Amino acid sequence: RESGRKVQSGNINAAKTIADIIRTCLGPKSMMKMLLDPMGGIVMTNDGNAILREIQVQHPAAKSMIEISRTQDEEVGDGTTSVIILAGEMLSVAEHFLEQQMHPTVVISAYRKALDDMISTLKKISIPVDISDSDMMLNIINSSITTKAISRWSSLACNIALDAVKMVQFEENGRKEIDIKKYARVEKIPGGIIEDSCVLRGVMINKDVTHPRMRRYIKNPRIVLLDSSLEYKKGESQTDIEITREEDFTRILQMEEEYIQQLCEDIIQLKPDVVITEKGISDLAQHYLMRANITAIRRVRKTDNNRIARACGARIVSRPEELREDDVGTGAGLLEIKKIGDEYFTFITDCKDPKACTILLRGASKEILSEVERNLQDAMQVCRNVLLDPQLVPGGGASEMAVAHALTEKSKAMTGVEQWPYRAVAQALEVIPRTLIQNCGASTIRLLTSLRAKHTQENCETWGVNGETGTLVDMKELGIWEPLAVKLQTYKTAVETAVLLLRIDDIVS
Amino acid sequence: EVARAQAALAVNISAARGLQDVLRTNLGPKGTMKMLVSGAGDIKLTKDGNVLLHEMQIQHPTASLIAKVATAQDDITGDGTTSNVLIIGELLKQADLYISEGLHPRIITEGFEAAKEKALQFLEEVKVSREMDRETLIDVARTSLRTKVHAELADVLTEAVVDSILAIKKQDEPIDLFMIEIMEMKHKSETDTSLIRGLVLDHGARHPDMKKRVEDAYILTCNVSLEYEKTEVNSGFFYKSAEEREKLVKAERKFIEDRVKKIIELKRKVCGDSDKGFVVINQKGIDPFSLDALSKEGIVALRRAKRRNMERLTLACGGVALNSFDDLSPDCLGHAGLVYEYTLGEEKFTFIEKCNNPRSVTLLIKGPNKHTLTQIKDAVRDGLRAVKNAIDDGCVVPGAGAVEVAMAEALIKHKPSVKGRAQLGVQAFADALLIIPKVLAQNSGFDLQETLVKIQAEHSESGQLVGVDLNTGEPMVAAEVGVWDNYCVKKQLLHSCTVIATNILLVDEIMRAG
Amino acid sequence: MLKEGAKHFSGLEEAVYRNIQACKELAQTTRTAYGPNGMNKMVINHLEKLFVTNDAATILRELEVQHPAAKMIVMASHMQEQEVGDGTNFVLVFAGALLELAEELLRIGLSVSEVIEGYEIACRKAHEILPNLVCCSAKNLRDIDEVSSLLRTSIMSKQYGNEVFLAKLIAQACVSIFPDSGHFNVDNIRVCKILGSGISSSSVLHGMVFKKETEGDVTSVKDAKIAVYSCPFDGMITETKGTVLIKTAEELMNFSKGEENLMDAQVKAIADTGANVVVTGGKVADMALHYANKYNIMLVRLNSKWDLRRLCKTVGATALPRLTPPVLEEMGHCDSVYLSEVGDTQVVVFKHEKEDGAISTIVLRGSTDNLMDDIERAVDDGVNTFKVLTRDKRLVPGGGATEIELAKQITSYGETCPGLEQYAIKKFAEAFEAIPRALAENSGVKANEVISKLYAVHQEGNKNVGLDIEAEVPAVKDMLEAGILDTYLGKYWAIKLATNAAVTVLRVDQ
């Protein structure tokens, strides 16, 4: 039970401090807040998503801030800090005034037009990419890794991100939307080195299949994904009574044989060696296949088989009758039990569809690998974000100072009370520049007013202050870049986010 | 509960001084001991930076956080944790002064680094490459032990130190996880510090007078049961089967008098005499009557050994391990040119000594057996790692602040950037260096100012590395003096000092929650 | 601290102020607890047991202090007493006195190491002229008056009154009976108090004195195969039945009858295991005893662990509960095993005395144990004040005469040495007057009178004080020339051990 202006305050109130301390933590140049547990447990992070947690949370809109944050933590995970900045910016500025000017409403609307102007300006301020040139992509990843200051192994993982994620990218609604991630498969591996890893075709099966009787290598036998229903039928097509006695053992187990084979001969109809048996797994099912000298890999996940559905690019087959390569094991394909470290790894490569690879990771060991993987995970996603979005923007204040002018130019032209949000919208761009001016550790009011001028003539197209260069700069020469969507994705959120709590005057239990 | 930014940094920097200050002699011979009766609530004695940290249950995050990274140096050097804390808060003292006047917390943290380099560059510049001899290591030994204990106490310690590492320098292993074998002994005085190029055997055999002086040591380190057990034991044990117990009574001493004969024959094979000493060491119990048979053969047959000792036995002697004594060649068992089975107190601690190809060298200390006897053991043992660094680095420079000024000089003597910006960081940065001699000199004596202008002008006049007389307060050529910084030690803690001081400068809030 | 942090109960005030005072109050207690004194200090045990002693460790052991300051040092007086007899009551007060000069130096603002070393420096200087203070040595450890001259001191160093016949009876106890050549035994020399008669009636029976009742017939033979048992007879019967008495009735008459010949069995098997005496940490069993009277096995109805200890100790015995026919493990040692009556109580006696296995067991008669205890306190020390294990002890003046000797000496040097080192070395030779001030109190005079003359007597190695009227006006006794002397040894220790901590205890501010 909470009300109105006090909500509206608690909106501005909480969302203020919500938007805040992690901006000290923001920037490649940053300030890590300390976090103390009531027991005395200490934490040092630049991660708001992490910072969101140990702090005791009460304000349910702060919980809701954690929501769009986690919601964004789901999407990128980076900028979850940066998304809640601007809503904090947004909710702070227009709300109290314009609610004391009596409305969420004109505030609500104008962020539609706060959104589009930049969305427009985004397509203007962001420039297309070569996803064709991975180096044109690499610098982004070279840029993506280094705000949290990780380079060492990532410098390679940068490239390896480029490689698979363009391949792990095959997806179409017919408008060809590519979100596809789960295709990309990663491998914890002991030994090798962080500077040695790769992407192997199909989907390499690492996690739950070490299984040594897969044989080892499949030259061109098929791998078989069973939504069969390979389960032995104790009768003709059915499962007869159990075996409590000698008579039920002879007759029933015999008919259990046929249904395995007749399907496994349908499996043989696509000629495998490896059959990874998921539905209809039977102790006779593998044994027959093992009697068939068909290695039947059981006690297995359909997630593996979904990895294997993306390992051969295939589907999994409920059809008992007439099992096919294109049914399961699409394409010639491979299957190989590989030891990277000594861990057995099934590698099912050569998906029937091209753009087939999945990321092998070697560190000097699992951990220093996990160093790669975690950062590669960021590296690899920026790809499918650049692969998502083949436009990208000179960052910092360039990203920031661009639209406010058009926005103010709107507010000036729009000259409503919607102009007031476009004023409230204008400088909210510049807070991370303030943080960037924090990042350099300089005088913001100057650099703002300075960068304000930098948009008066240059129009801050490439010109922000970059706290890490310290100065108002071209962000193209300087090379500050993100795929446009990510900018918007950070930008889209806070609008709706602010607009979200812009709706709430009422908490009620 | 929360404190923001400025209020956040205070609790940080404010927590440092008093904490930091207690250590103002933790280093060099002037270093003052500190006693926990309070750490777990137990009477103790310690000087080290990192160790004292972990020892006390230390409630404050400030106290908490560096001990984690202070663990690194104490892991690496073992000392200079006895040092590093001092520059750190003094560094913390410096940066605020700007922000006190005002300045952006970034740029100061920002201005430490080229500073952290140009000074580290000066380390490259100042580092004194030295060709390590036992004497050089003797004065390397005593500079870390002066940090620990009396230079007096550093003396009898120094011997075993540079001597133990002396046989590992043979091994060409720059680090020592062996010849780190240390022993403590019942005594009225912790003064005694003994050096066994071999090992020392804690357990005595339940039978005395077996071979009390083993001259030629032929050591089979044996897991063997020469006590299977003598009476009813079934698998060697009691059980619920009489039927099996009925069968299993006799083979026991048979399996034993086997291993008896397996030693009996072995002894006479190893020896053919009681003249050449001989040793059997069981990881488990042995029949004394086995021993009785064997104790009269010229063996010292030993029992219930500790698997750890077995190794240095298996290794420093080149010893061996079997489950059946069988017979083995005399040489087939590892060797120590002498074994001295030694009782001080009521327990014979057998010295298997000059163990052939020692990879391990045993350092006995006899003492009152108090945390006194502890305060000596820890003392040598980080100096061991310290002097180990002198094996590591060929560059050892003197301590006693001979480094600091000349290092603090340049970056102050010129803005290394010729930025105020960096010099903001740098002047903050390069200043904290002086904390060590300036307090120690004043800890021991006159105000820092003189020695400072001395040591500076001296270095300015000299360039020779001149450092405090750590119980006077006057600078003395610290190289010749022997108070000595491994280029390992100082460089690391340098990094350690700064690498923490930044993001902790960067804590602009702390919430109590989790 | 300022923060929530770490662990310390010393430092700041505590180190300077409160530790020194923690280094004070108990030394303050020990001041007339050492040396010739009429001071007496009541103490209750964990037993709540009212007792008086001028011995420290007794008092010490039950004292708890949040500081290590008072805490840690007392081990030294023990480390001392580990070495010798008293002088221990001197050990700490020597420290505490010389200590609080440093907090003054702390007021005067002298650095720790600056304060530290001059003592240590002069601690040598003490030990350096300490041999110059050897005015005699120990001639006949067999002689009574050779030894009694000494023994009087630690007793005196404990208490003034009873010292003489003690110092006599202790050599009449024949500390003689050992070479004390490096061979000396206070396991073979035990103080066993008979409660009864007088303490002037207290004797010394050479051979183990066990006031415990000699049970039944005396030893089978005097080289006693000894069965020392914690519980040799716990009873052989179990009465649990329908009623745990009778239900089927005749089943009762079996075991109460069948019990006793099992006690016979055990006792016969005491005669069968071969023990010339059986020893019961547990109870005697009467039939067994009667059987042991038949078998004439000497017995002890009940045995203290203390009994069993010395029993297990010296016999080579092992005290065991036995519900079984017994097994000699304990066997023998003592070649004469007797019954005595001293204070007219059955005294189980064990004597092998070889001059090496030689047992001279002091048997204290007295009508009070607290009496014979505070006695035994000084008696504890005299024997092990006698125990130097130098037959030649380089006898140095007793009673503290050597103090003023080096007061002049080392502060005259303390004069000569320069710097802040001076008062370090100077306060050092000032540490003596404490007890010459302390006992001067119980003596009844100020220490200036004492010390000015103790100074004006100058180099003596005799002239000194204590509890006396000689200790009052003259500031002169013979703490050498009267027969009151000291071994050279504990001196070095009473000097050194305290000097170490006083140095060390300050250096720790934690």
Image: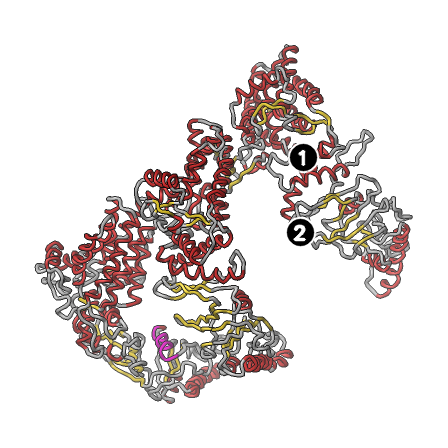
Which of the two labelled residues, at mark 2 and mark 1, occupies the earlier sequence position? 1
On screen, C22 above or below A89? Answer: below
Instruction: Tell me the subunit letter for badge 1.
Output: A
| On-image quarter of the N terminus of chain A | top right
Furthest residue in direction front, as rendered: B461
SS at badge 2: loop
Instruction: Give the main secondary structure, helix, strand or loop, of the magenta stretch.
Output: helix
Residue type indicated by callout 1: Ile
Please give left or right for residue B78 compared with residue A19 in the image: left
Q: CA distance from mark 2 to mark 1?
A: 25 Å
CB under 8 Å between callouts 2 and 1? no
Quadrant of the drawing holding the C terminus of chain A: top right
Q: Where residue B315 sits: x, y (%)?
A: 55, 66
Helix, strand or loop at label 1? It is helix
The magenta-colored residue range is: C306-316
Above/below status of C78 relative to A465? below
In which chain is the residue bearing label 2? A
Depth check: give the residue in front, C323 or C175.
C175
Type of colouring: secondary structure
Of all residues, the one furthest to the left in this rendering is C473
Answer with the quarter of the image where residue A167 lies.
top right
The residue indicated by pointer 1 is A141
* Residue appearing at x 53%, y 38% in the figure: A44
Query: Which image quarter: residue C196?
Result: bottom left
Nearer to me, C264 or B407:
B407
User: In front: C165, or B347?
Assistant: B347
Which residue position is annotated with label 2? Answer: A191
**Residue B63 disc label:** none
Residue C207 showing in the rendered view: yes
